[PDB]
Length: 308
Image 1 (cartoon, rainbow, N blue to C red):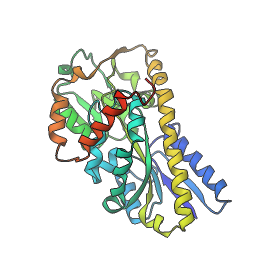
Image 2: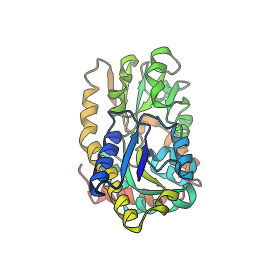
Image 3: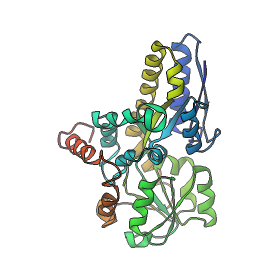
Image 4: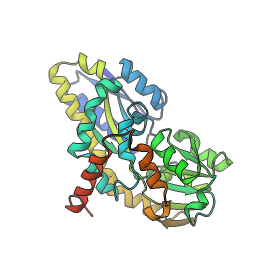
């Protein structure tokens, strides 16, 4: 079968490369019985549209933000608790935990997809066209976000003016004033060159940003038993591989952003004042897994079960 696999990420992105590597390996492991055609850069629609077509089976596969999935399955919001992870290595360990993996079980019924495992992109950061010396400087700033509620709620609690906007429009929106600031990770600040029009780069690491490898449940049900196992395991391997890329490259992309001539500052959780507490109150009855995920995260850190 010729499967199609969609992403919203551009061609140089880690996820796109992982999807291509997955496709090549599936072709080889299947002896040419199967192939994967990869459609990056939103070619097949926006992420919400892609999820709709995974649900029907019109689209076979995707490497999708957990952000979009959280619009369909609000318990996925638990991953976005601010400062749940202290860094990308902690995040990867959280995403590999039994607690995290258990949360995948609801996806066939709740979203019509099989989630094979988690990957990620980078931690979230803030770029602004103006000076930012305290959280108060974010007030009223039109601030680009990924279109999902956890991040909307965070910026609403901060008093910014969050504005959902897909990746391709962001560079231009900064260049032309449709936004004053953006929420984005270091890989894409580099790749999309969004630092060019910004004044200040804040390395806040305020939220993680998981990815999930999805197979349409309808399509999965049509696979042979051997292929269900082989394809899901192979996809899981490639999704997991992304965690190791970010573990290595996150500080490298971050250091690259000290060489673009802008004001560069690191901040920590205290910078955000009461916004984190407000987020917790919003999400307490939306994402029932949060207390267990917080416990898992705390235990991984206390036991030093990752590189730090």
